[PDB]
Amino acid sequence: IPAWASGNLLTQAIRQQYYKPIDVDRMYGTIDSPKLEELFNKS
Amino acid sequence: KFTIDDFDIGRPLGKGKFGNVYLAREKQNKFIMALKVLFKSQLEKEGVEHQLRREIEIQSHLRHPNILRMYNYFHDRKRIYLMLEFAPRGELYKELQKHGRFDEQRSATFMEELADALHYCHERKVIHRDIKPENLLMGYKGELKIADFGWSVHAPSLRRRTMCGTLDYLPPEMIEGKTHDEKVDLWCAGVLCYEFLVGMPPFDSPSHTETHRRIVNVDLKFPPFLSDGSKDLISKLLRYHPPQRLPLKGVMEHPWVKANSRRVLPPVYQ
Ligand SMILES: CN1C(=O)c2ccccc2N(C)c2nc(Nc3ccc(N4CCC(O)CC4)cc3)ncc21
Image (cartoon, rainbow over all chains, first blue to last red; front, side):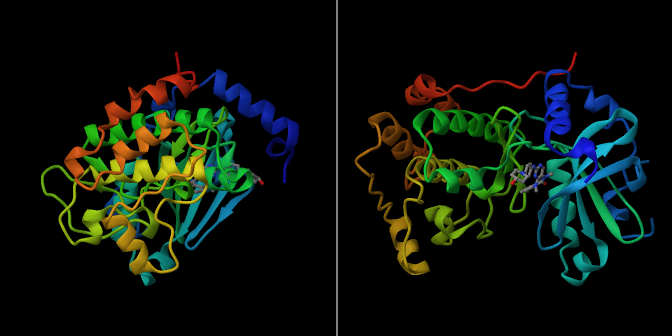
């Protein structure tokens, strides 16, 4: 388990994310996704 | 465009049939989320490919503070990866088991958040069909998150016929072999409210047929410790006739909900 992922570093990082949310729609929702038809096909 | 190397893997969060969720940090934004990892071969052997596609299609198009968000997804040679919102307080069923039952404030808050999410789903003709504690998670301040859409359906026009959900939560109409609609979720919300407050579901029995019997007779027996407001809300949701059940807007506006909910809306980006 890396440090960021346990005890205090984690809670700290979770709190920051909650009160300072990012534009997840811009950051993630504008990014390409595989077609649902391609999911069980060649990557 | 994403791949597994875009993420630092932190620790396992839950094992499961298909089926492992990890705490993960997306590298370039240092953003903490969860990755659900599925094995392509196992899914196909099990013949659940269309099942999973439909769960992904539904949940990836829903954006609501009380529905667990699917930001994106990707796949490699052997695995499908779902990029999901991390619910830092974990499984609601675990918390219910730990406490036995929830107080009215906690239950009313969860009820408001549930009705708001389900209303968002119904606005879009999505019926969830399997609301129960095990399918709910909790956010940083305890906010309910509808987390699993395993029985869910987008149902624009046609009523439905599929018996689905969980024994203790089944609406009379499913048991009776009638077609159903979105009002199934109203019934399951009443079951949930009861289980929140009592710790057992209302039609608990040794056998499937006795449970079926208690459900179709709406054989509801309230323990004496419940307030009149909580019984009033449960009775208005657990109605034999789907069209007589309290609408979700009705649940949010219910006096017992207004008087007891301490619902907080998560901060939004801007
Ligand atoms: C994406 N996703 C799911 O798709 C999901 C859907 C349904 C059921 C479970 C799920 N899991 C495992 C998830 N768990 C958590 N959060 C989470 C947070 C904390 C904890 N713990 C609290 C108690 C400690 O003992 C262990 C850690 C567990 C799960 N966030 C997102 C999850």
